[PDB]
Length: 281
Ligand SMILES: O=C1Nc2ccc(-c3cnco3)cc2/C1=C/Nc1ccc2c(c1)CS(=O)(=O)C2
Image 1 (cartoon, rainbow, N blue to C red):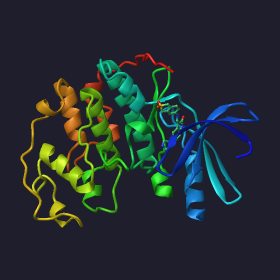
Image 2 (cartoon, rainbow, N blue to C red):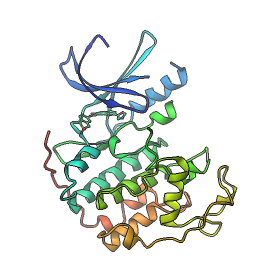
Image 3 (cartoon, helix red, strand yellow):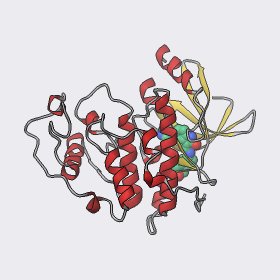
């Protein structure tokens, strides 16, 4: 703590406040996260600094002193939420959307292969730099330890306590649609409102499309029954390749939902390139 000179407060996270800080020693600029300490967390967090991938925000150090916990992450200047706000008028170019989705899927495939889940993916957690790269931040913290519910998977909202890697694919699918249309896909303001907004778009799930759904802890036979909408109306003007991938990312049944690995081979990415975005820092 004493070894860092806090510059600015980057923002309040799910498990603590994040500050832009300068390592008074090395002089390097980093992201200092003050965790708002169990031995389990310590061990879990420790394994995370071993995970290294170009599309994952690197956990540099873990400072456990005076019974306090500080996580030191690599620093990136902008998150996707701010970039989207800045591109509100023209929207993000499709080539850049495709590049970002491609890199994010690589990041997830890597984490998923190590059995590490994010569980709370959202625009605020996706950081970008001037080189055209995008990285996932806060990976694996959920397991170690006005909340947005917009990117929450159906199985989580229905009471399933043993979620899988599929929950991250759902969140990513929601973010994908948002970049294309420039509007949140399911902006619920409560757990039931979130669930109903999903049902009104993709249809109320039943035993046909999702075996075992009526046995979920929070499922109620009294749920209204809405018909499914066509994706052409939900995410215009995404082409057929894109709509195809999106539908596979938003399948109700977690077991039918596409994996990050398989999505990487989807036809939507046949013409992927790596454009450099115009960032205003
Ligand atoms: O560079 C960074 N590393 C991080 C590690 C974790 C988190 C985080 C998020 N929620 C909880 O934890 C964030 C970072 C991080 C931040 N850099 C950064 C730096 C500046 C700005 C933003 C983000 C947002 S903006 O409005 O675009 C300005």
